Image: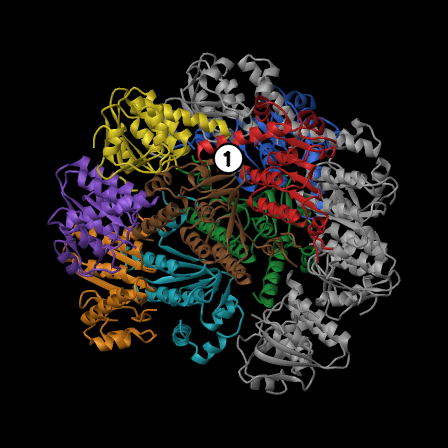
Chain colours: A cyan, B orange, C green, F purple, H blue, I yellow, J red, K brown
């Protein structure tokens, strides 16, 4: 990792930029939550920018990150570079309305590649969040989350996951 | 871990914030106890904030941390992000009255997933602590600690683990 | 890695030089994207220089890097040292017209050494990008991408991958 | 493995019974093909019985086994015990008409959990085989092979994979 | 491996059947050569049957097996089940004229997935053998051995690798 | 380990605090002895504070630490947090009279979970040290050192291991 | 290894056939020497046949095998299948005059791919053996033993390693 | 590695000295190329010194380093310490005329201890480079590249690899 | 290891203190020799203090350390904490007369838990050193070095290894 | 290991032949001793033949085997094939006078490549055995056992290790 | 292990011979005890022969074997070949009076290379057994079991461990 | 490694001291050569001191170091501490005349514990260097380099390896 004593990621964070790359798990979630809290303490009015390039991850960590993004008062812009699959698509769709962007050669997946009841409760939570942020019906979300396929930025724009491309 | 020579966790600790993430064991307990002691030596009147995202851990380490939190004179606020299960739920319920908070998509579990007598003594200790801090009866605690299930923040509010959500 | 507290790569980055060496995967793609973004934030008018010595990599990471290079407003010069094979040949051909260079003893390969449909979509994307940047027909690209062989800088000049050697 | 110098599987093979259990790969395919050839050499008029309990496998091995079953002149009965998923469902549906059976608590899956073109040719081969043996249209097969779900013996009976249950 | 004290492969060898499955290397070549020598010593007039299901292997072992098949006086029939790629396609094409067979769902590949001169001499040897047994020209063989693709039994019939399907 | 260039443990050592956590072995003993020597060289009149959370360790290392504690002229206070078992209980009982403290939920164990004569000699040494510092008789010590059980701070107060709780 | 209770190699040994395949080391040398001794004890007048397919090995084991071959009174025929390199070429050339054979697609190499003096003595021993059995001069042998290349059966016929091909 | 915050290698690089020690592969080639580029950017008129102690490496990395050395405008002196074998001998011979030096006890070897055609093209490239820089004929180079032996500095002086010793 | 940028061991070395802990081998010997040389270069009149807690080690390293201690002109004090066994007892006894100290609970062992003659020469060297520094006869040393037992500081004082305790 | 239900080694043992190949350690010694005891129980008048191809081993195992050979009443012939080094040379020289043989290309070494006194006693035992069986003086044996070199059968004949070659 | 379907050890056991070779642990003890029980059930009047070549082992297993030997009614002869150290010397001395033999080049050791009290009880048990079977005094046994040295058969004869040599 | 930001080795290098400890291989040789070059560039008139404690190493690295020491113009003093064996004895003897020292308890060994000709040429090189620097005859060097033994400083003084002790 090249340096600028700052690293490249710390130099980027000086510009209020959080990078969510690679699989999402508990350590990544903790680091992202800490970065968001630090950025909010620096200022609660300035926008934040998130760049997503992720193959997916765990449901609990993604839900924690989503809750933290919805808690703070700053506007948040989300940009898809490369991949946004499974949990990354939730974060991409959870940005501020009018501030969700993608690059022309990006793929978006909302299909998902403890006991038997907690998994059902978490899945229903995901359905409700997706329906709230996409403005679809619940049945449409359950039907779409079952097919194993990717989407282009124009398809995701028609669905309701993105605003511009 | 991005830096700010401070790291992100040290930058947070400058704001009097202790982070309890991941499984709780002896090393984590020692680090948390040292951080709490240093924070108290800095000042014995200012509040402290703890953020919990934990799947559980060992009983001895959790009891040590609970004793240290009850020893110092500072008020302590507890915030649940993500998960609070097994030993993390004890720490969540052990905060100062009126200062126990949770996020809307959080799951709370009080069920627990040497010789034969020390284990029973530690379990009775846990029952007594839970009954003291939750204001339930002992029989209710023993019955609830046997079912394998999670709780929503509203259920934990009705039980007595939280104050607000 | 010799130092100059700067390293040799950081000293080179001070001169606006990005080095793409070794196989291309998600970590390399993330580092290169971050470096390009930081360089653009430093200035959006100054040229950038990229040096490629790569045996290939993953399609998604190469597409992400290609999209980032096409997004920023700076002119980009590409220089082949050693090898440019598979994904590295896309980056070599994607530079600014008139600013694509190679050394006399370099080998260039465009042959490539999830479900069954996403692979077809990514391959058609590659065909379209290659045809756009090389000025060949699509059939020529699909025919050439099937033979297992390397090319000299003069053959790559005749094809359309390079501008000078 | 209990013995009867014969083992239990050899004692079963004395009754003209071939067992296809566990994941299907090249070694399993070779053993099954050799057993079928030996059984045919013993007699080319007597029926054979196959018991399938398999989570899936490789396409090439399943196609080889299917071709061998279609080559020999003996009638073949197929019985599903437990699981028949991915490649096992092809073998289950490829039995002699009127001789395809399942147990009441069995799950059947036809969704599938080299270069880019050979995979597509093999997929089209699978579509044609499934449409021939199930009596569906090709579009129905491609639509059904995309959803990630299992089937009950009554659903598989309505589809055309089974004859009785 | 089920038994019949004979195994299934030894029971098959009682019927004058040699099985060439899996990758071809020195141990496999030695076993196949020993089996062919033993079969010839049993009788030098009776036919032999070979079944090929192989992804490829080493050139030296395949050349040794080819030489042994060409040495003995028995007629040899070759049957493709599943795969015949790289070195296995040489063995498939090297059978007795009029006795080279394949199954309808089989894939045949003749492309190939010490010092610098011995490799070239072995390649020229392969070109000469292929041209002799297929009745093509040398230039056609060199051109075809460069494209990375598989063939159907009808294409291999038109080329000259098979006699019937 | 969070920093304050000081670490948290070095920041604590600035306050004259030595932390004895985890199993006690030769490396831990050497570090603790060096810290005690450095603290004495800083001043030979100021008190020192030790915090013990230990499951036990080796007899030789504990004896070395005990000897170093008894050598220096500074008063030493011992505080039990969590666990004090086997060798940790020796260190807890070896503090200055009137300066041995414990937390309400702490467990204390004195039972212990080369040739045959050195082990017995070291055991007699332990018996003599315990009898000297606890004010029991030798027979009481050997009887209590045999039962496999833990003690509460009130039982340890009655025995003579602690002064306050 | 298929069986005939005899194995294929034991069935071959019934026909007075010794197989020298794979790298030659101490275990292989011991097995071959024991087989040759047993064959001589069975009869001291009947011929023996050896088939060589070997990439090379250790000098001491090859010298032991050569000495055992020269000791017994039986005629020995040597046949090259596949490869005869380094130590295998010594065994190939050490057969009875007029009884050294090779297959048309075989490669023969005589170049070789403790203290500093024993290695020189062993090399001079090899030079003397080669010159004796090939009828070349010592200088020719030392010159030829230095070039890194293989030979065809006609070249080895001209040199003196073989009698027929 | 002793320091002077500079290391010993960085302190040497301050004197315009590049050290090529150990086997040459892609990482070493990238580091050496970056160092040469940085040195040229510091000044394009001052000489550079390279010390070679290398057993060999990969052809592609050595060709990349050779091309970079021939590209820059600075004079380059090459010094052999210890070993210069295989790829290192190319770098030793590729220095500026009159500036190629060796130590009295050094050994130089030019013998060399993808598909079948690319290796031949790379070998012919090596032959042409060696003939250009040594002033031998191509046949002499091909003959000398086959013998497995080392050379003394006087022999390499007579050949044309060195200028002084 | 806690810091004071100095570490605890470097802070101790500022007070002219060398710590010999753990097994003694070549790396430990080299570090100790370098520290002693640096301390002598700082001053050749000031005393040095060594603290020994060691289970033993290799004879050659201990002899090297002993020779270095006897070479320099500074007085040296030796202090036993914990253990001094095998090679550590040599270092303990090799200090300046009147400056060899031990703690009350320390154990001292002089029994020791290439070709056949070098071991005997090294043993005779050890006997001579021990007899010189302890003032015993050689026969007493050889008799005592055979029994497998430890000693108390009073026994070691009577023997001649220590001066005070 | 080829079979004859007998193996090749058991078939050889039927002819009263013991094979000592590979390094000599405790397991090999136990097997050889058991074989010699069984052979003696079969008959105490018939000769036994031993074949040695060994690089050496442990002194205790070789001494045990030597003692067992000297105990039984049968004549023993020793034959060197390949190597007889270190412990194997003792066994070779310990055969019955007039019955010690070697092959022309064999190397013999008598140099040898607990506490410090037992090694001396075992070495003196070896010297005495060698002097007894070779008819040299002790000083000659100790001088010869120090040089690192091998011997030819003629040198070993002159020394006294062999009787014929 | 050569066979005679019997192995060499089973063939020896047919002659009433038990072999105790290698380290003695629980598995070896169980096998030896089972063999002794089987031999006694075959006949309770016939002698048994034991051959010892052992470096030592665990005290509990040796005591179990000693008890079993003392329980059965058969006479037992013990023969030392090679080594009898630690636990093996107990078994050697525990044979029937007048039936304890050794070979001339054998070494015998009686020095020995849970809680602290059980080890002492087991040691006192060993002292009593040794004094009973050797006819020494207890003090002599304790003194002799401390020196680290081996014994010759004549020394063991004088001590009382053997009867003849 | 204790620090003084300098380490102990860098602090020593400030005094013009190079430490050659442990086995000598290519990395150690490169570091030593770089240190010697840096020291010469600092000054070409001041003396340098080397301390050797080495068990040996590789011939090529030792020859490279020897050549570098003979190249520079500074006087060099060599001091033996501990061991100087194999390649380290060459470095010890290669110092400036009158400046070769050893400690009283040091052992010196000159015996030494690719193809077959390069090893012999390197050995002859070693013989010539040793004879030049020791003033012995070549035959004496070859005879002495064969015996496996060490030397005392007085023996090495008589030989010619040292000047004082």
Left or right? Give the position of A54 relative to F30: right
Q: How packed is label 1: few (under 14 Cα within 10 Å), some, or many (20 or more)?
A: many
Asked which quadrant contains residue J64, the reply is: top right
Q: Quadrant of the N terminus of chain I?
A: top left
Left or right? Give the position of C103 relative to F102: right
Asked which quadrant contains residue H135, the reply is: top right
Q: Is residue H142 above or below residue A35?
A: above
The one of A121 and F9 positioned closer to us in this rendering: F9
- The chain identifier of the residue carrying mark 1 reads H
Place of residue H59 in the rendered image (x, y in percent of width and height, measured from the top left): 63, 39
Is residue K152 something one can see in this rendering? no
Q: Which residue is mark 1?
A: H35
Is residue A101 something one can see in this rendering? yes
The one of I140 and B31 positioned closer to us in this rendering: I140
Q: Quadrant of the C terminus of chain I?
A: top left
Residue at 56%, 57% (x, y): give it.
Answer: C59
Residue at 45%, 80% (x, y): give it.
Answer: A139
Helix, strand or loop status at disc 1: helix
Left or right? Give the position of F11 relative to A163: left
Place of residue A117 in the rendered image (x, y in percent of width and height, measured from the top left): 39, 77
Left or right? Give the position of A32 relative to J13: left
Place of residue J139 in the rendered image (x, y in percent of width and height, measured from the top left): 57, 21
Q: How many tags in the picture?
A: 1
Place of residue F165 in the rendered image (x, y in percent of width and height, measured from the top left): 14, 57
Residue projecting furthest to the left:
F98
The one of K165 and J139 positioned closer to us in this rendering: K165
């Amino acid at each position: 990792i090249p340096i600028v004593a700052y690293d490249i990621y710390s130099r980027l964070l000086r510009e209020r930029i959080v990078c969510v790359m690679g699989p999402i798990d508990d350590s990544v979630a903790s680091l992202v939550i800490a970065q968001l809290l630090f950025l909010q303490s620096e200022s609660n009015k300035k926008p934040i920018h998130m760049y997503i390039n992720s193959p997916g991850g765990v449901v609990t960590a993604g839900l924690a990150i989503y809750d933290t993004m919805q808690y703070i008062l700053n506007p948040i812009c989300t940009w898809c570079v490369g991949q946004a699959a499974s949990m990354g698509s939730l974060l991409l769709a959870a940005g501020t309305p009018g501030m969700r962007h993608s690059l022309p050669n990006s793929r978006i997946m909302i299909h998902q590649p403890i006991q038997a009841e907690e998994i059902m409760k978490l899945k229903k939570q995901l359905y409700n969040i997706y329906a709230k942020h996409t403005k679809q019906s619940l049945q449409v979300i359950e039907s779409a989350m079952e097919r194993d396929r990717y989407m282009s930025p124009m398809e995701a724009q028609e669905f309701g996951i993105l605003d511009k491309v």
